[PDB]
Image (spheres, coloured by chain):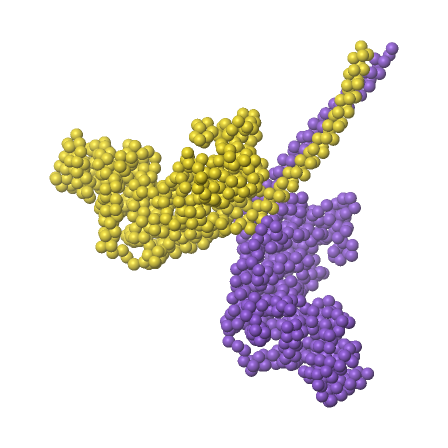
Chain colours: A yellow, B purple
Amino acid sequence: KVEELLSKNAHLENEVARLKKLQKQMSKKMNDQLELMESNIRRDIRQGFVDLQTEKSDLIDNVGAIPFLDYKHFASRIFFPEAGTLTAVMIRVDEKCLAFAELIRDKQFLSCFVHALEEQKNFSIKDKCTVASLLTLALHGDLLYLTEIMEDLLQSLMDQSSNANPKLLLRRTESIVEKLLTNWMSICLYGFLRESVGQPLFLLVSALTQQISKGPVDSVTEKALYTLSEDWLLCQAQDFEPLKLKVVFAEEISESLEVIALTCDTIQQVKEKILQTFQRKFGFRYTQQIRDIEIEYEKEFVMLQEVDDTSEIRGHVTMLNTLKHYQVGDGACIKVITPSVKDDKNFSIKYFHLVDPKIKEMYLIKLLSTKVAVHSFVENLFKSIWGLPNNKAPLAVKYFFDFLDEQAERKKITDPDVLHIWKTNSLPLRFWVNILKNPDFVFSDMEKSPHLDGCLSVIAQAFMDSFSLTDTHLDKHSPTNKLLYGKDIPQYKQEVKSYYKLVKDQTSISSQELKTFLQEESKKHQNEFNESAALRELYKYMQRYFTEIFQKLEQTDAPSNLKENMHRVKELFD
Amino acid sequence: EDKVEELLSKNAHLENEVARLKKLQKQMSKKMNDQLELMESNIRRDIRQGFVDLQTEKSDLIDNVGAIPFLDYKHFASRIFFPEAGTLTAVMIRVDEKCLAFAELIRDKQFLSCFVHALEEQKNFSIKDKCTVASLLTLALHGDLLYLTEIMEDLLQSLMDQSSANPKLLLRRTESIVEKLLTNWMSICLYGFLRESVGQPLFLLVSALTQQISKGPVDSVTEKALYTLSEDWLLCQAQDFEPLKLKVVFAEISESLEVIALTCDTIQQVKEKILQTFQRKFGFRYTQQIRDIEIEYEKEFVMLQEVDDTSEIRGHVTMLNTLKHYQVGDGACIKVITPSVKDDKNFSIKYFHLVDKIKEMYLIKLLSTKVAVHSFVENLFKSIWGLPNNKAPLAVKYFFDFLDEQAERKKITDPDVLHIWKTNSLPLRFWVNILKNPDFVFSDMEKSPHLDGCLSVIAQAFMDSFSLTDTHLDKHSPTNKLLYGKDIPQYKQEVKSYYKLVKDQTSISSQELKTFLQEESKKHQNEFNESAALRELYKYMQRYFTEIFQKLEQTDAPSNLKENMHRVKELFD
C-alpha cells in the first residue's frame, strides 16, 4: 500500500506545482484584461467628446415637394385612433338618413341629445369620443353649424359645474365637447399644418432618421448609439468602421451612387441606408416598396442575404449577418436591381446582433451629440408651430383664442394664468403634441419605428414643457429626457407667452371671413365622407337612450314638430 | 519498512498546501470580481455626475466689484518695455549738461535715423539689444510722442520699401528696432482705451476663471484641478468630496458670512476661498496681505494649521491636512481675526495632496468650464475689437489708415496682405500679451501657473480669430483647439468686419491727432527720469560711434550736426 502512497504523493506534489503556476497565469491574465478594458474606456470616452466637438452639419437633405397623406386618412387617425371597423366604409337608405340629418341640424335637438347622453352613469368616455367623432363626420359638410353647436356646448361646460377651479378645465378629453373640440382643431388647422408646420416636421423626421443612421443599431433591442432618449442608449460597446460603398443601379445601364454604411450593419439595414440616401439626395423613392430591390455584392457577383449557411450560433440564439461577415471593404461595388426575416412571429427570441449574456453612461455624450445635431430642425418646427405667417395667426386659432378671451371675461376672471391654462389645454396639448408624437398620420409612406417614437417622445415632452407655467429648477435628480432640453425651455416659455399675447392683440375675426372660411373648408371635403354610415351608427345611440333624450327635451320647452320629428326618425329606422 | 509513516506525514503537509492554495486562489478570484464591480460603479457615478453638471450649471459667477483696481501706468509700461530684467526699471520708475546734450541730439530726425539704421546694420547687434535700445528710446522720448510717432513712421516706411520678398511676412515678430518701437507705441497710445473698455471685462474674466476653478478640487501639489480649460491641467485620479457651507465670522464684536468650501481643501485653500468670496461679494478685500488673517475652528475654540502632529505619512511623503481631517461638518462656524509651508524651497518633493487613472472621464469638465466662462470671454474679445460710439480708438484708426496708405503706395491689390499686416501689428503685438498677462494691468494680481495655462487656451483662440485660413476640425486636433473650434468661425467674420469698419470710419484730423498725442505726453511727462535712460543709451552710442558717423556722412549731414555728435561724446567723457 506504499505504492498507492507514492502515486498519491507524486500526484500531490505535481498538483501543488500546477496550482502554483495557474495562480500566476490567472494573475497576469487579469491584469492584462484590466489594461485592455481601461484602454477601451479611454478611447471611447475621448472619441465621444471629439465627436461632440467636431460634428459636421450634413443633415442638409433636400426634398422639395412633401408627401402629405390624403385628408381622409389624416382625419381617420385623428377621429378614431383605435378601431377601424367603420373608417374603411366611411372613406370609400336615403330617407331615414335624410330624416336623421334634418333632425340633427336643429340646435335644440342636438343640444338636448348631447346633454342627455352625458347625464348617464351608464355612459363611458369611449362612447363619448365615438359619438363626437360620428357627429363631426355627420357635420363635416357643415362646419359653421358644427362650430356654433360646439360653442353653445362649451359655454354650458364652463358655466355649469366646473367652477371648482377655472384652471382644471379642458385638462383632458373626457366629455363629448372635448373630443369635439380636438377634432375641430384638426379640421380647421389642417391647412396651416400643410403650409407652415408640415415641411419642418418632415425635415425633423428626415434628419432624425438620418442622424441615428450614422451609428450602430442593434437590430434586436432596436437600440442605437445616436438617440435623444437615454432608455434607447446602447449598453455594451461596439467595434466598427464606416464604409464608403459605391452602389450602382442597373449591356446594362449605368447609375453610380456613393452610399455610407458600417461594418456592423445587417443587410436590411444597408437597404434602408441606400433607399434613405436615395430619397434624401434626389427627393423621390427609387422603389416605394422596400421589398422589391435586389441587393448584390460583387466578389469577383454573389447575392447576399440576411442569414446563410455560415452563421455563428451561441447557446440558443443565432447571430445575424453583418458586413464584416461578407468581408466587405471600403469602396465596394453594390448592385441594386429589380426582380423577410423580421416578418417572423418569433424574431426577438431567436436572433442575435449586439447584446448577449456594460458601461452605458459613457455614451451620454451621444444624446447631447444627437440633440445638438438635430436641434436646428426642432426650433424650426417649434417656431413654425407658434408662428405668425405675415403677422397673422391661422384663423382657427385666432378665433378660438378670442372665444376663450370672451368666456374668461364672462366669468369675471382677473388672472392671466387661467387664460394661459385654457389656451394650452385646448391647442398644443390636444393637437400639436399628438402630431409630433405621430407624424405617420400626416405623411404618406411614413413607416415609424418604436425608437423614433421614443425620441419624438422626448422632443414632444420638451414641447409640452415649453408651455409650462411653473418654474422647474433642474438639479441632480431629474429625468435625462428633461436634462437634454433643460437650458432651452425658459426661452420657449417666453416665446409661448408672446405667441398668446400677440394673438390677443391681433385684430378680431370678421364674421363674414369666419363664415367664408368655414364654408370653404366644408366644401373641400363635403363628398369625402358619407354621412350615411355616420348617422346610421349615431342613431344606435339615439335609440339606446331615446326615453332619456326625450325627457330632457321636454325639460326645456320643445315644440311639437320637433318631438314629432324625433319619433318620426325612430319610426323610420324601425 | 516504516516508509508508510513518512509518506503519510509528507502527504499531510502536501495536502494542506493544496487546501490553502485553493482557498487563497478562490479568495483572490473573488477579490478581483469585486474590485471590478466597485471601479465600475465609481466610474458611472462620476461620468454621469459630470454630464449632469454640464446640464445644471447655475449662473453664480455674477460677482460685483465696481471700480477696477488698475496698476499705476508706471509699472504697466515697466513690464511691457522690459519683461525680463528690472535692474534698470526700478531707477526710471521712482549730469544736466550731458543729459540735455543727448536729449537735444535725439530730437533731430536725421541723427536718430542714421543712428537706428547704422545700429540695425550690424551683425554684432543682437535682438535683445535692439529691443533694449528701442525701449530706452521710448522712455527717453515719452514726453514727446509726436516726434516719436514721426521717427517711428519714417522707420517703418524704410523697413517696408527696403525689402521691396513678400509683403505678407512683414511685422511677423519683434526683431528690428522699429518693431519693438511699434509695440511700445501701441501700449502708450492704447492704455487709455484699455482702462476705458477692456479693463473691466478682462478683470471680470479673471474673477470668473478664478471662481469656477475654486468650485472643484485643486491638487495643492501638481497644481492640477478639476475645472480647467486645458486638458493638461485636468486631474487624473478621482477625488471623493462633498461641499460645505461654513458660517465664517469676523471678530467681542462680530460679522457673519456664508462661505462655500470643500471636504478636501488644504487650509490655505480655504483661506483663499474666504478672501475671494469676500472680495467678490463686497468689492473690497478684508485684508490686502493674505498672511494676516487667523483661521480658527469651533468644536466645543480651536485653531487649525497646514500640518499638525497627526499627519498621515506614506512611503517618504506627507499628506496635507484637509477639512475632513479636522472633521469639519456642514455649517461649521469659523473665526477670523488679525494677529506658510508653501514657502519651503523643497515643497513639491516632500508633500502629498491628491496624487500618489481615467482622465478622459473629465473632458466634460473642460466644456463645463468653457461654457461657464464663455459669457465673459465673448465680452473681453468683443470689447477688444469693438467700436465705442462707432469710433475706434484714435490710435487704432490712425495706424490702420497708415497701413492702408502704405499698402496703396506699393500698388498691392490683395486684401489678404493688408489683413496680415493689420493683425501682425495690433492684436498679436499687444492684445495677446495682455490676455496672457493680466497681472501687468491689475493691482494685487496673484496669477497662478494654471490660470496662465487657461489664459493661454483663451489667447490661442483669440489669436485663431485673426487667422486667414479655413480650419476644418477633425479627430486629430489639440483639445484646446477642439473646445473653441465651433466658436472661431463667427469671430473670423467679426474680425474682417472690424477691419472694414475701422477703415470706413472718417479719417483723423491732424489737429485731433496732435492734440491727442501731446495730451498723452503731458499726462506721463514726469513719471520717468530721462536721465538714467539717456545714460544707458549713450553706452550704445559710443559702442558703435564710428559706424553711426559713417552712415551720417553717407547722407549729407551738416557740419553743426557732426560737431554736436562729437560734442556729446566729449561731455560724457
Q: Residue at x 72, y 25 (%)?
A: B22
In the picture, which quadrant includes the C terminus of chain B? Answer: bottom right
Name the residue nearer the viewer: A532 or B171. Answer: B171
Is A408 placed left or right of A15 in the picture? left
The vertical placement of B177 against B57, above or below, is: below
Q: Residue furthest front?
A: A251
Query: In which quadrant of the rendered view does residue B138 lie?
Result: bottom right
In the picture, which quadrant includes the N terminus of chain B? Answer: top right
Residue B46 lies, in percent from the top left, at 60, 44
Residue A465 lies, in percent from the top left, at 43, 48
Residue B556 lies, in percent from the top left, at 71, 85
Query: In which quadrant of the rendered view does residue A360 lie?
Result: top right
Q: Residue at x 61, y 69 (%)?
A: B167
Is B190 placed left or right of A248 in the picture? right
The vertical placement of A372 against A289, above or below, is: below
Is B75 placed left or right of B396 in the picture? right
The vertical placement of A240 against B197, above or below, is: above
Residue A245 lies, in percent from the top left, at 52, 42
Q: Residue furthest bottom?
A: B560
Q: Is residue A68 visible?
A: yes
Q: Residue at x 53, y 50 (%)?
A: A55
The number of numbered badges drawn on the structure is 0
Q: Is residue A229 visible?
A: no
Name the residue nearer the viewer: B141 or A136. Answer: B141
Is A424 placed left or right of B116 in the picture? left
Q: Residue furthest right?
A: B1
The vertical placement of B192 against A212, above or below, is: below
Q: Residue at x 78, y 12 (%)?
A: A4
